[PDB]
Image (cartoon, rainbow over all chains, first blue to last red; front, side, top):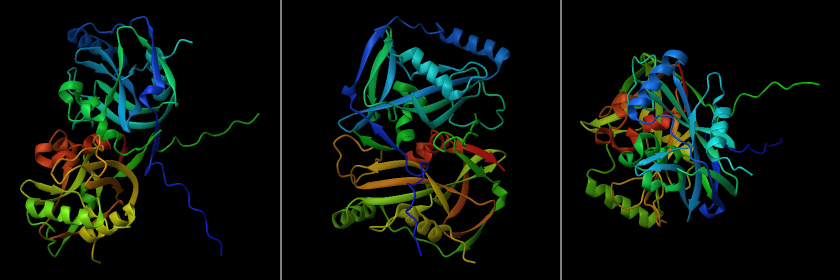
Length: 202
Length: 202
């Protein structure tokens, strides 16, 4: 004759994420962090050299979200007038994805004095060329890079240490949406990839 | 001194979905199902009339995935040369989202002789106009429509009953990706929204 109290709905169906105000977050400076590749030519030469040695490049990137006036903003690292990146980078062979992303974000943003429970997408680079796709194209059996994106939940407050040559910016979703010319195909589709989340604006 | 066997990784982090070959699926015909709105003018007039009476329109849509040669395809309903839609429609006031989507897909596709565990995105229409966004734009406190998308897991085999005036097609991700001119902003970003899933190609 008993009834059961119903379980919290699956996190697959409704995923809630706490956001905090932009003003909860601050940065201090650290020494500059220079890009591994000094040009487009060097980038693709290194990708080719490493592909021959260790196979497909495995990149991981973190999407950290804050709000201002109840609108989500994604944290980006500005390196040039039109050059923005997510905090992340290249995994070492054998390295766990999530543990690697933790290492990489400590390297880039780690204060000098991470909660990663959510995969938000995957992108693949079929050739030693710029184009990347959110799927493996037909008959591509050996992509040259696989990029995996994760949502990194921030604490209520945090201090970041930012390499001097980077500017830590908070981009509102309307800045990113349908703005591949400004931010590229991955960052510009973050609004779509974040749309399923139930955000709490603390 | 004991060690614990580790739990399956969270479904938030790695979400696996079984797909089956296109040839596992068939359709039979039923009577035609006419669009509620006969023109763009009538569409926005009805949206306005109903907004005044019952508030924001609540639409729900199902994303059903199959594969051919290990490439995902999304099922769409073709109504015209350039007019494709997802199976779904408008919720009744008070109606549960998932139960409403089940009702709507039975209406459209239900054989005459649903597993919905995943939210994949949200879109909002700020005005009585075509544009829709994957977020609520700043200072929009009363959007006119909220569209919610769900992944509908298919059984190994299924038979569909399709209104005579619709053609059931299976669209590969490369047909959709960066093809808003062909399919609109929602269907064209399905490849990005599906990229997080670990698909098993049965």
